[PDB]
Image (cartoon, coloured by chain):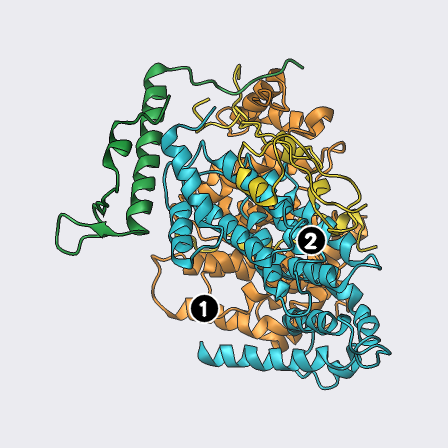
Chain colours: A green, B yellow, C cyan, D orange
Amino acid sequence: KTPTYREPVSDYQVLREKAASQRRDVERALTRFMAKTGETQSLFKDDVSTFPLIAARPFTIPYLTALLPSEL
Amino acid sequence: DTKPRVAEWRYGPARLWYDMLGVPEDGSDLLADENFLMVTQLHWEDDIIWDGEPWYSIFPIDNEDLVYGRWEDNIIWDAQAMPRLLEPPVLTLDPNDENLIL
Amino acid sequence: HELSVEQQLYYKEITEACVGSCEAKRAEALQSIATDPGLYQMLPRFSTFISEGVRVNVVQNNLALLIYLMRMVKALMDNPTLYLEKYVHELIPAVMTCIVSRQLCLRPDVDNHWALRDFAARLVAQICKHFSTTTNNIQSRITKTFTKSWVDEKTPWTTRYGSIAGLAELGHDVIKTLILPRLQQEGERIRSVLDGPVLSNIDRIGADHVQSLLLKHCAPVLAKLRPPPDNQDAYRAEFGSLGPLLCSQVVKARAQAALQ
Amino acid sequence: RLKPRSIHELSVEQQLYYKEITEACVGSCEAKRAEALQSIATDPGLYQMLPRFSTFISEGVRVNVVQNNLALLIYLMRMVKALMDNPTLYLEKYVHELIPAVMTCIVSRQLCLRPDVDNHWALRDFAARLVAQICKHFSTTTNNIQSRITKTFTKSWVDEKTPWTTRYGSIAGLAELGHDVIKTLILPRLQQEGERIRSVLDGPVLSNIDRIGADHVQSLLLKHCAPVLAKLRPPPDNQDAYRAEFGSLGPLLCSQVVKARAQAALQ
């Protein structure tokens, strides 16, 4: 009656790969969701499914969104 | 006993529900066993295939809460007459699950 | 342990898209949840959000937000990449709360709590088809809760409707060995339908909804375990109506055979 | 907050035991199999490992009929038989996985060479029909298990233009169901059996498995009909009265009945 555990994956290569691919997938999902539910642009003629761009909106005060840090 | 709800976080997952509620800060014979055996409740005939065409665990480890816990005690049978008082649960990030970095 | 800003923003946008500002952003958010590859590390947050939001129905009996949370669960189930085995113990009682609770409505008479009933019943039949293992005992423990909620008297017609709906979405052998012994209960139902001292109460609409669901689901069960003639099966049945429904079901089966 | 790292409900001695028993039960060596089968047949602590054994059986037969690997199947059926006669463990929680595995051994087509191992194939259907009627003997409640497999066997039989492997297996399965079952079911169907035999005989096609299937089915049906007759009538007019039943077994059936009578006299 000696207990056993699950196989732990302590490998730096596969941990870097997992964190990288999860970050890339969540940022791709976020940008496709935000480009689909708003005004969109396109590099190609009538191209919304592949490479959708969030449309450029003008700010009333652009230095506040440019120069200010968001994580501090 | 009447359940008016209670919230202890307003800052973790479900903060949107807590804010909508406005809870500030931390302030708050057919029951015979055989009937339920899956031989008598499953169309296992569909499975029959006709003319088809260990130092670390070998097997996976199941959710202890699903396998053992009485989750049935979180079913709200009557909203007004709720037998016990439910309390807000904090996120517990289980590390047994793979696909979670930590 | 704490979500990065990317996925924190994704969690915020996806959860606030399913609260009800417009329908198109909701459909794109549910099509995001159903069809993205990397949504793990945000599954516990979604499970907590859904279970707490279904709990918040007791303070505000909002039918619409419960329909939105059940469509969130139905979208979470259709994702091929994420495995809900470690988090199903949270989503099972939320869908169960959407099934067997009694006040699902703010105005009980006009709100169709009835659909959030059969939608969540189909959802729990799917959640115990995909995940029931003999170590889990999910389906047996769900049938036991539905059964002791149905056989026990004093239960309201809404929660009896939810119990019958879930039991009848589980399959054919379940309605053979759970529903069909208590068909005499239909007489106890028709006690309060064909002859009620109080007609203007809210028990009559729930009772004949229970009746319609019962005879709709027991018509193919009567078509499976009876003779092909069915001359006075309705008379032999309770109230003589279930038997008419069974005759209609046999006719429908004949029509399906003709189409084949 | 992180929930504690859970442990599997089997010990590592138990998990190693499961690995050794399963790698012995795939029959690389026969003495290893036989002990592992006796170990399954009398280990008292083999409960709480039984989900993993049932899942290994079920999953195995389904990916082992993708290519019809007869030994893999004969070893798994012997593992099922060794699981059943163990008195300690509680089996009818797992019989919903066990029964469609055995039905598949009996009612399925053989992807590997059709002849030669058909002799074993009959035994694969012999071992499967044995464990099938042992499962209908145990685990019995009202109108769930025995009647369900009886209905599937009968609609396997009355189905027109069957695979003859499936036909032979279903015939064996309905045959081993006891005294009354052949007394009430095999009776109104002799003419169909004879017509099927006549079609295999007429069509020249010999390189298919239809002729072998037909001979096995006819022999099995004739033996069952022999005692079904020895059991409910006197042995008078055993020469040409069976010609009222299309003359299939006739005097040879009468000789089988006489051998049964001699065995009864010896008893």
Mark 1 falls within which chain? D
Query: Can residue C123 be seen in the rendering of this structure?
Result: yes
User: Can you identify the residue that label 1 sits on?
Assistant: D161
Residue B72, compared with residue D184, is above or below; it is above
Name the residue: 38% across, 57% down. Answer: C24
Occupied quadrant, residue D19: top right
Residue D229, compared with residue A17, is above or below; it is below
Is residue D225 toward the left or the right of residue A66 in the image?
right
Would you call the spot at circle 2 few (<14 residues within 10 Å), some (14-19), or many (20 or more)? many
- Depth check: give the residue in front, D86 or C35: C35
The nearer-to-camera label among 1 and 2 is: 2
Occupied quadrant, residue C160: bottom right
Name the residue: 64% across, 50% down. Answer: C57
Q: Look at the numbered disc 1 and give the secondary structure of its residue.
A: loop
Is residue D118 toward the left or the right of residue D39 in the image?
left
Q: Which residue extends farthest left? A: A44
- Depth check: give the residue in front, C136 or D80: C136
Q: Position of residue C194 (x, y in %)?
A: 80, 81
User: Can you identify the residue that label 2 sits on?
Assistant: B40
